[PDB]
Image: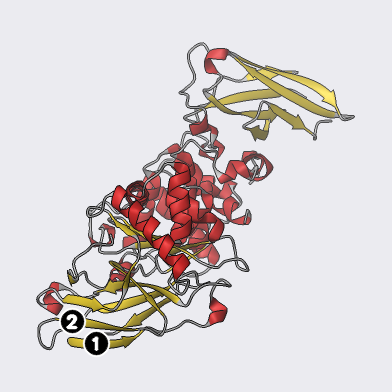
Amino acid sequence: GSHMASVFELQSRGNSIKESQKRKVWNFQDWQPTGYAVKSGQVITVYVDVEDGKPTPKLVFKQMDSQHNGDVTISLSKGKNVITIPEKPTNELRPGTAKAGVLYTSNPYTSEEQGRKPKIRIEGAINYPNYIKGIDNDEEVMNDLEEYVDLLKKDPQLPDVFDVFSDKTLVNVTATYALNWYKNNNKLPSETANKSDEVIKETMKYWGFDESSEVNSDFNFRYISMLKWLDNGGFMNAGNGITGFNKAEQGGALGVDTGWGFMHEMGHNFDTNNRTIVEVTNNMLPLHFERIKGVPSNITRQNLWERNILPKVALDDYDKSLLSHVAPLWQLQLYDKTFWPRFEQEFRSRDIGGGSWENKHNAWVMAASDVFKLDLSEHFERHGMDVWKETKEYTSKYPKPSNKLWYANDKMYLNKGGVFTENLKFEAEAKIVNGNDVSISFDIDNENKNNVIGYEISRDGKTIGFTSTNNFVDHGANHEYSIVAYDNEINPSKPYNFK
């Protein structure tokens, strides 16, 4: 908050970049609050106390609303430091942004390295509004925001900034937007902080950081979501443990939006392993956040189950490009929610994957097979991946699944149902349409209506399709049909046959 101690004692928090690399995440920062704002070109005086000869903490100046992160690292020496605040190039900043920003501390050393905790004091800076979980209260900080927005009007050279520090995160937005958003929405910064922490917790659980080993343990970092000037770039961006969002998304940030846009960026930050294909695998994170909220996954949103995946995998003779590639892995995660953390754990701690596109694909098949104790070669080759003779040899040490796991789809959670009851009754009816197509519609009993995830269609003894919908059009009939319904745990019904 804006009435904090002038002398800060700094924890020796270790090098978060190095710790990151151990765990294959993308060089997370570990910025810690000061609550001070500065203008580019102003002088500040910083007093630093460390044991003689020991390494000193650093100051981070962060310019507001850059197309980049906006940070400059400022080195400090023991004793007095007369510092001129630096200035970012004008052309990097959203038009009309003051040359100004805020100070954080970075202290990337261990106790053993640094000795006694550094103490620092900063003179000549201005307090900007900020909430620090465990320190601040909502009433005061809202008052701080009211006061600072007024001060902004009087001195437009000051940075338009409000920060929320949680245990594990930083949310950086403008003060003017923050004040409006909290008031109009009847919300408080304490909630921004608590929700941010919940996101990191859920993310790290999903990724398999379960404290089972060093590469699976938490460490000292502060994940950062910050306002960036992204008008010309993509919608949002990622890197270095930072999510960037544009002006209009400040409310998403403060609300701790867990929709596709935000979580896709966090996903990029949580895996850099060059042994895998992170552009594919990082989508597992936003998909999960969709599922845990009951939201139809992007795979449903892009109509890919029906357009791409399900018709492809059914046949017996075996932005969106990326969802197709992730589909087989998502299906395994729909089938068993313990899959992904364990899969991530394998790639974090084992000499697997690497090499070409195709080599990494083959590694997924082997790793997923080990995790499940199932021979998943068929599963992956049904998605159109080329599984090699040796991979099949490797995986053939396990039994094949007895379920057609490639029929998994979002209905498995969206139904909020169970398995087929003993009373299951379903029927199919064919009509000839559009000239000479066979249009087969499906009806199911009321008790089982939310137990079904789709129907497999066979003709003259060959599987010709699977749809998660109530209708299938057979465009390729010149015939006896056989229909098998599938439930939320991918169990088949008895067949329904007609001629």
Which residue occupies 58% across, 51% down?
323
x, y percent for residue 344: 38, 55
Label 2 CA crowd tier, 10 Å (few <14, some 14–19, many 20+): many
Residue 377 appears in the rendering: no
According to the picture, the residue beneath numbered tag 1 turns out to be 81
- Compute the Cα span from label 2 to label 1: 8 Å
According to the picture, the residue beneath numbered tag 2 turns out to be 48
Nearer to me, 421 or 262:
262
Label 1 CA crowd tier, 10 Å (few <14, some 14–19, many 20+): some
x, y percent for residue 36: 31, 70
Nearer to me, 50 or 308:
50
Nearer to me, 480 or 248:
248
Nearer to me, 482 or 471:
471
Disc 2 to disc 1: CB gap under 8 Å: yes
Image position of 79 with respect to 10: above or below: below
Secondary structure of residue under mark 1 = strand
For the C terminus, give its image quadrant.
Answer: top right
Residue 140 appears in the rendering: yes
Give the amino acid at mark 2.
Answer: Val
